[PDB]
Amino acid sequence: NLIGRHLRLGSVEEQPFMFFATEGCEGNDCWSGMVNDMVVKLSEDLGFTYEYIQPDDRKFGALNKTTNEWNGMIRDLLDDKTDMIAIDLSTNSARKSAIDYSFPFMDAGIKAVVKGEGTTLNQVLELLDQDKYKWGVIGSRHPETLLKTHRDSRYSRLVDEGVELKDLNHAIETLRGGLFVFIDEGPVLAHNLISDCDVFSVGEEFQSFEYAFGLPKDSPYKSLIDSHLLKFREEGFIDILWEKWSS
Amino acid sequence: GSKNLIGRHLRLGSVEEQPFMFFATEGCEGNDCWSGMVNDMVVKLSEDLGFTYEYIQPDDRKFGALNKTTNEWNGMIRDLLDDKTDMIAIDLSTNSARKSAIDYSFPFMDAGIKAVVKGEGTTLNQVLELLDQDKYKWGVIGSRHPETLLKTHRDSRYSRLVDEGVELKDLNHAIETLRGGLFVFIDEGPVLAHNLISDCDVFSVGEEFQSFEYAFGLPKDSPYKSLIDSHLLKFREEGFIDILWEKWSSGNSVC
Ligand SMILES: [Mg+2]
């Protein structure tokens, strides 16, 4: 079904899933990481060519409830600028209302972290009842969406009253600045903070979701992508790649 | 697209597999014979999506595997392929053999293969050690997912394990045989965790291995997959699946 086809793949840098070199490379060779290794193997086995297309707005994607419009990689997919989103794309109901997901490749949860040993914070909602710590989530990323759609609207308060963060670099910078709880995703934080010995978890992880690829509704490629991703998991390839790429 | 589930009557494949499904064999009729985590999910789905349903068990009482001699399926998988059912509503493990013939819903639970053992004295650290000894017997249940995963593993020593193990008919027979002693039973983590909670003389053989999911089974080209997938994702995101596991899975331990 994919032999000879060309796939336009939405992606962005998100270590260790994807690394994007901004110079010293051309085309697909600018990309590396766990997801890139998956795409390369898919392309070899299924016989397609591909390219990566980043959203101009550099966002993952969320639905703005004021305008009822999407942004980020989700929007590029809906606009038919891409055929599939190849990244750690978290599963949530808002996205599911607009796009499909492939078979998942990894489980993930929401994790909150803070700099400084011995934090008094036991659970993130406690942030609302104090002013020693600031906190935040990154705009147009999955954790913001999950917290805003949580049944307990105190999670919407956390988002609305938090610091808006531009991207992962900005968030980690702010975290490393102290007195700041950053709420994001376990696997991304596990990598990326491996060497920050003075950064600690706040509470336990919460919400259970998956990382998958994103597909447009009625994609003719979903069946094959799903089958091959399942085989990757069953054969141990996903675990081998995580061991290869995660610090 | 246009087709939804309102007013449809679904035939759902299932069998008893505690704590996912319990089937009463007397003193009940129809859907009232069924209870468990999966039943609670189906009830909620039926209310939200507007379908009625019944459960249909395969006569062979198998989950389903592909016979490489005949190229035919059995169990719930076969019933689905034969249009006796519309969806398999159970802890249906994801594997590539099944995926060649059917689709899966969005998953509801992670699971792994787990090996357990009863016996005093020397014990085992990893299942392949079984091949180089004769103190312990061992087995997997025929036409169930662990057998399929071991038979398709690229290390054919796992096929030896299956081929040289004792034949087990179903979960009751396997647990019976395990409790008889000097036996390694290789099955699925969540199933064993629930059903062996009180067996203080049953221990692990190594760590869990192979990661897969439990999902519902759907025929290829089902007009209902999108809706079922969306609703199952919402169940997970809302914490409903976790609440049901806490409701149904065994707690405490006399051990
Ligand atoms: Mg999973």
Image (tube, coloured by chain):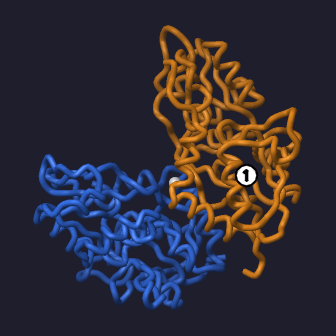
Chain colours: A blue, B orange
Left or right of A180? Residue A29 is right
Q: Quadrant of residue B60?
A: top right
Give the residue number, with chain letter if any, for mark 1: B89
Farthest residue to the top: give it.
B121
Under circle 1, the secondary element is strand
Residue type at mark 1? Ala
Label 1, ligand 1: CB separation under 8 Å: no
Work out whether residue A104 or residue B7 is closer to the camera in this orientation and state it. Answer: B7
**Residue in the image at 49% along x and 20% along y:** B124
For the N terminus of chain B, the quadrant is bottom right
Residue count near mark 1 (Cα–Cα under 10 Å), binned few <14, some 14–19, many ≥20: many
User: Residue B154 location, x and y as percent?
Assistant: 58, 45
Question: Is A118 rendered above or below residue B129?
Answer: below
Q: At which x and y percent is residue B238?
A: 51, 60
Judging from the image, mark 1 belongs to the subunit labelled: B
Which residue is drawn at the image coordinates 50% and 84% (left, top)?
A77
Give me the residue at 32% from left, 64% from top. A184
- On the image, the x and y values in percent for residue B175 come to 67, 23
Q: Nearer the viewer, residue B138 or A102?
A: A102
- Taking the image as drawn, is residue B63 in sight? yes
